[PDB]
Length: 50
Length: 50
Image (cartoon, rainbow over all chains, first blue to last red; front, side):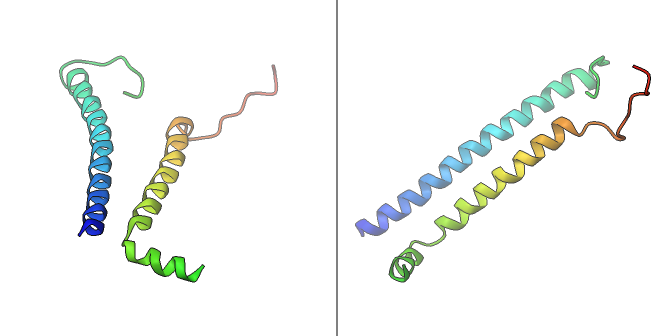
């Protein structure tokens, strides 16, 4: 039971760490999308290729 | 070693997700280089007069 508990805890910790990294990436994309909604939809942008 | 491989098979799929993570990083590096440098459609050239 100790062996199985250690293995399942290691796998679940790996899942939580991967979810945290993906959450950071998704938060960066959502910040970019919020900037685009504030600057393209609500105004006219002079930034090139934006 | 065959005995180490037989014991490593019992741990499940840690190595598959490690390989998937490294493959994702290796694809993302080329995506970074392509999205930074390849922003031009045609390869321009300067005239022979300098």
